[PDB]
């Protein structure tokens, strides 16, 4: 073959097809995992300032990050983590959370290593492990049993201590923790994080912790960073995303925070891949964090206002989707909620599709074509052997304009009353 | 061990030391490979327009490129290459030329593959080959005969056919071509490209061609793209950089052009690493290319005016550097020229440095600290076994403001009085 063997089995991109099918129908697109409204004015203004300020901002900045950005990341997150963070040794600016994840896998995961992944998982964790020669090892959150009185909560999806412990071996290099979780919206508790911490310390494993949804927490639930737990800083890489923080997904700026003895290897990958991140977006992100640090916990702060606003959008969507028999699982965080479609699988078992195509994928195509609503089938966030079991959930994104939620309700009205 | 074996031998970054030392002294920085004056107005205005326009430009764009950008790249470079280019199948937008190179190496280079690299080489080609499991194989340009008191020319650094042919084996996967070359400023001739093309076809080898300095050509020399030669489109990946095209290195936008059967593998790497490139800089680059396509070959176009202006800066620097006994090699393209320091090595051999330290590295440190001028030791663009033999050149960048060149002359006049 022409191509490298590291690419085996990772060429299929579900997202390219998802975008394709939605674009051919008249839809309310609740599949897109980004806002369809503007970022806050201070963020847009920050980028405007960066592209109209010191003309030298048009030229290269420092390899490991624009210094004013690494300074504020170290200060702001050092406070939150209860850790002294050196900007030069403990911070790397990357091309989004995606680039940060990729850099961590390529630095640490080697042929034969195992990587523990928690289902449902942000889908790239599996192919990134594979491309680095690692063997993914899956542990499944166990859905809470639902009574048809009250809706389930993401919090009730359990990480079984015995099942998790049994996944660790001498070959475990890393465990990937995503909290708040996409697609499920689970916000991991202190007790759950202490379990993960205990096993990572026992087995000398690195925890790669994807915290992009840090600020998107609801119902009084608190984001806890595993790197803040005793002894965890020295074995944790913590990842963030400016796009998910400031509702500006197209900025594609992210970072990794961690101890020098691990970070040095990520710096090695960085300097031998992209070398620099763009200068001006970094300046915009630095200015945006400065604004939020100055207004920390205050009523006008984005980190106070925005999750409150999005909690209302969540509640609106939860009520609306029930009108057609979808069963939401209330998320404690993230942009997302999932709905159980088991009643549809029961009443409408035979949908067109390919052999061994999970029901949810077939259902989403049906719903797009017939009802004009887009969701993402949750089976894409499962290992292939588990897709036959976890085939009855779909993911919706509620971080949407009020007009979009109105349009959703119009589709639901038609679904209920027409034909 | 903690880190992946793919990182072996690639952790050392010479650029961090160079940048650090220069920041610690009063200097005219001719080591920085980027302009110290603004990008052209139309380019800065394009970015301003992108960050103040359609608010949805703040959110994710398409994975393989912002469609207006891939459209104009395909149209414009299609015309330049004499090639029908499909924007969806033949174009990938990347995080600069660096990201483009990285994507190519990770898609195609596998364990045990040989990659032919031409010395002097842009330094990342070697470690990128190594991280992909490849074995770098070096062919060395031969500096031309030092003639009748005249300065050397980059054109006369020869690519010996018998040497090059001897480097091709059944294990050769790719050859990396950089034209115009950094650091040398050589613009490869049609004959030289035909030599490379003939061997790539004979041995069924892919040519990765780094053409970031495409527009920076002088003295009537023409940039020829190897992908435009008969039979080469099907085996060539052509790389460019928006930063080097529009004098905006901090934008970090690049691209790869090539046939689908190769590009599909680069897309696999892309979707499993960064996933998206930032939206708004892509919009700026698209607008900038649209401007230049409309004015193509006209006197008011940047691609005509800018290299003409920079040729004047080149000529100024060539004259000035000779005043202290540095011997420039006249470049036909790129931002750079190199000067022979052999007369200094001979008359001043005993500069402080480590036991094995190439003379040029020692000379640059002495020049920074004592003469107030920064250059880059050319030995960093050689394989380690060859560094002791090519230790007598340093690289200057002439793409500088009038004021900077005046400042250079002030340093040089002070040096001359103390030769
Ligand atoms: Na262990
Ligand atoms: Na061959």
Image (cartoon, coloured by chain):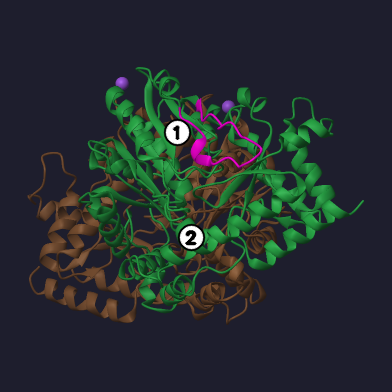
Chain colours: A green, B brown
Picture quadrant of residue B271: top right
Residue A346 drawn above or below residue A190: above
Camera-side residue: A364 or A109?
A: A364
Q: Quadrant of the N terminus of chain A?
A: top right
Location of residue A30 in the rendering, given as x and y in whole percent from the top left corner: 67, 53
The residue most toward the front is A149
Classified by dominant secondary structure, the portion drawn in magenta counts as loop
Which mark is drawn over residue A307? 2
Which subunit holds the residue at mark 2? A
SS at mark 1 in the image: loop
| x and y percentages locating residue B115 in the rendered image | 47, 34
Label 2, secondary structure: give it: helix
> Which residue corresponds to the image point at 54% horizontal and 46% vertical from the top-left?
A331
Label 1 Cα neighbours within 10 Å, binned few <14 / some 14-19 / many ≥20: many
| Residue A247, visible in the rendered structure | yes
Q: Front-most of B232 and A272?
A: A272
Q: Are marks 2 and 1 in contact (CB under 8 Å)?
A: no
Q: Residue at x 56, y 32 (%)?
A: A143
Does residue A154 show up magenta in the picture? yes
In front of the other: label 2 or label 1? Answer: 2
Question: A114 left or right of B16?
Answer: right
Asked if residue B12 lies in the magenta stretch, the reply is no
* Mark 1 Cβ and ligand 2 under 8 Å apart: no
Quadrant of ligand 1: it is: top left
How far across and how far down the image is residue A405, in percent? 68, 62
Label 2 environment density (alpha carbons within 10 Å; few <14, some 14–19, many ≥20): many
| Viewer-closest of B33 and A84 | A84
Q: Which residues are magenta?
A: A139-159
Q: How far separated are the C-alphas under marks 2 and 1?
A: 43 Å
Q: Residue at x 62, y 59 (%)?
A: B66
Residue named by callout 1: B132
């Amino acid at each position: 073959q022409l191509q490298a063997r590291r690419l085996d089995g990772i060429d299929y991109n579900p997202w390219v097809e998802f975008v394709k099918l939605a674009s051919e129908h008249d839809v309310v697109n609740l599949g897109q995992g980004f806002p369809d409204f503007p970022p806050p004015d201070f963020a847009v203004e920050a980028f405007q300032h960066a592209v109209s300020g010191d003309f030298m901002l048009n030229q290269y900045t420092k390899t490991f990050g624009y210094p004013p950005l690494t300074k504020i990341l170290a200060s702001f997150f050092g406070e939150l983590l209860g850790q002294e963070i050196d900007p030069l040794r403990n911070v790397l600016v990357t091309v989004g959370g995606y680039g940060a994840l990729f850099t961590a896998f390529q630095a640490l995961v080697d042929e034969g290593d195992e990587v523990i992944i928690i289902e449902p998982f942000f889908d790239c964790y599996e192919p990134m492990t594979m491309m680095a020669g690692g063997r993914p090892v899956f542990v499944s959150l166990k859905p809470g049993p639902i009574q048809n009185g009250e809706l389930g909560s993401s919090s009730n999806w359990q990480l079984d201590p015995m099942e998790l412990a049994g996944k660790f071996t001498s070959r475990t290099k890393a465990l990937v923790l995503n909290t708040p979780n996409n697609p499920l919206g689970k916000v991991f508790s202190r007790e759950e994080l202490e379990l993960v911490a205990s096993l990572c310390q026992q087995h000398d494993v690195v925890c790669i912790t994807d915290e992009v949804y840090q600020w998107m927490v609801y119902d009084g639930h608190q984001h806890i960073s595993i790197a803040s737990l005793p002894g965890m800083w020295e074995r944790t890489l913590t990842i963030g995303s400016a796009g998910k923080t400031f509702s500006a997904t197209g900025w594609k700026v992210g970072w990794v925070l961690g101890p020098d003895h691990i970070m040095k290897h990520l710096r090695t990958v960085h300097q031998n891949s992209v070398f620099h991140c763009p200068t001006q977006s970094q300046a915009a992100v630095a200015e945006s964090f400065e604004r939020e640090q100055l207004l920390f916990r205050q009523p006008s702060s984005y980190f106070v206002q925005f999750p409150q606003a999005m909690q209302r959008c969540r509640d609106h969507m939860i009520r609306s989707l029930q009108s057609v028999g979808l069963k939401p699982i209330i998320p404690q965080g993230s942009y997302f909620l999932i709905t159980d479609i088991s009643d549809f699988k029961r009443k409408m078992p035979d949908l067109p599709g390919a052999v061994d195509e999970p029901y949810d994928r077939r259902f989403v195509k049906w719903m797009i074509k017939n009802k004009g609503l887009v969701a993402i089938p949750v089976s894409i966030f499962y290992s292939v052997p588990h897709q036959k079991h976890f085939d009855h959930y779909i993911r919706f994104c509620f971080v949407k304009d009020e007009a979009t939620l109105q349009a959703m309700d119009e589709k639901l009205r038609k679904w209920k009353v027409e034909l």
